[PDB]
Length: 194
Length: 193
DNA sequence: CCATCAAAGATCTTTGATGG
DNA sequence: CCATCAAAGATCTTTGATGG
Image (cartoon, each protein chain N blue to C red):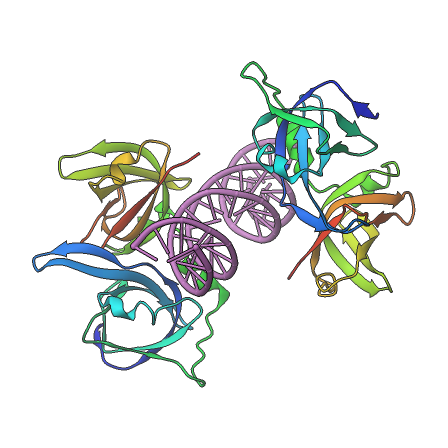
């Protein structure tokens, strides 16, 4: 928990493309990644985009001076990322690689604590547009949930019957009427069916 | 049973990727598909790869000047494939679409007549190599059968415990000791374990 | 830089497993 | 048999690397 100084050799399961978000300091860019050790996996927020070349699938790297909060790891300019050489292996079981790239079932998100990072592809039942926001009703075979997404050109093209890929969304509510909320680092891609 | 001039409306169940083979004049490309009417379904040999855009699942197409031989249909550059009108429905019952894509049980292949086209995914019992061909022993819960496959770098990687994908294989032997043979247009893929 | 084309990832559907 | 959902195949979309 908290800041982790020691080096943590990990394999990179997924490395996404750098995107830009907004803060009080103005435009900033980052990229989402998913890395895993032998025991488990973690979702990674990399605020330094110059490390994109260092994060590649099938590759083993060593991360030090990073942060661990709840459902993910924070890698920033103050951190250090190195490349493995020989002795470093980090064999990840088929189960972890699988569960890291899988969409969690809605019914399972009700037993999850608040602050859980939610990534996956979900079906869209109803789309309720708000002033500064867009309310999405998402569902699967195991149940239903409501997700608050950002309002933009792509998201406004989303309609009932489509799907949405959520990345680094947070769980703001659980149990009955579970809800997800879009954060600052969150990204949502709309997938048009048929 | 032969050359059919009259247009036959059909719905395309599936279309695989085009592949290359060798006979005499050299490389020739084609692809395997499956079409079905309301009455039944067929396996089609398409020798025109430009028809790949014409053959798509869920789409209703009209085929004319096509050859029906024994266990399949033939569509070449000499035939004509057009898009069916809006009044053209061709509604295929779920049981036909299901059966058309399902792997036939070995014990059922015994009752089938010689020349029947066999497509499906089977389990590998034992692999005995030959000179120009490979002998695959395949089995299921309903029995066992042997298939003669082509010899190449792909089929030599197949070992007991693996699974093979048979496409447009023919049944050369029925009853006891049933046998499948790889034809010129036949294709096989080795699925690992 | 753009426009090609080739390599890798994500998506859909039905095929076949799995539990009543 | 029925009902339910993920292995295999195919394709589009992303990416990445290459030539105009």
